[PDB]
Image (cartoon, rainbow over all chains, first blue to last red; front, side, top):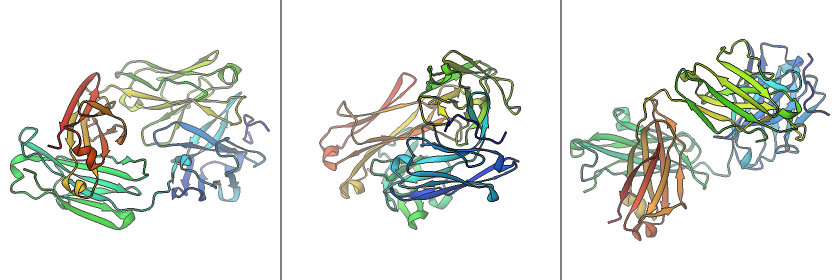
Length: 10
Length: 223
Length: 214
């Protein structure tokens, strides 16, 4: 669980 | 065409619950992560929470974890923030923001207009209105300052007029202070000809809709 | 704030101003991108700079970002009145549990008007408030520019901290500023001093108004 990971489809 | 429209804010006592909503249009809602951010009156921005586009992940600020839940309804293009166990320190404008991402961190490319959450244990109370009487030494050239002190009301707002809206020239109504009691006070002052103080009546009209109270206070010269 | 910004910057129209944002080795030093937001008074933040240096297409060419080591900076050239706002830098910190960290913000003032000294009016407690067993001194400050003031209270020449509440300056119709300060006393405190003063400092210069129970 990385809160800085891309949270979008693209 | 990108719209983020928030609702759900208002005044609640500590330990109560509120749900905020962020209704979106103009983009494919289900393709985007969304954030909540808050700002205490007069202070900086504080990130609150994120939800993934697919709802696979949710993260929270330490300051709200255990109390707030972020959620989304893709069929309604709507983001929610469930706020439980509200504390006075949760008082803030809450913003929703569309997630964007660059290379090594994220940012918010579109923001809602904000909704104000006020957490207070103060109860609805109409103001006490005291006259601020003008000088009998004429003080400040041919012009006297007189006013009304609007003390210990809750919540905002109050409106003030003079002589039922017929006196607007030289009126200054000051923004309220918030006291340690949780109640507001404000003042309105009007600058008038000293020569009028004999012949002209000055009445401040104070309206406090939240308590269904109106006060009309006559302000008479001292000697 | 993980990210340190100057509380305030100012400049005159046409000037260049720079707003710094200082982090550390787990945020800006770690290579996590920095972004900037503009917040016009009473409005939501708006994206100004993303990925350290990029302007959204809607942002004028007067706004630019740079990043070196543990620091980022926003530069505004050709300063205009419309630029008067709070500016926030934003990144990510691997040593904290949130998606975003913010700077504390920088208030940008555009000095677009001549200096204007404050008008000060001090009212004593009304005999009705006293006759209702309370006492409020009211110090009303108006028509000053820029919108920074200090208000201090004195009882017989001695400073009073307890019972004071002061509003932040608020902009008027004429683009000058107003503020108010209240001092809450017992009628006993009011009657037990020869005088009270409201002392208003604006750009190093002070107006003091006194009232006397007398």
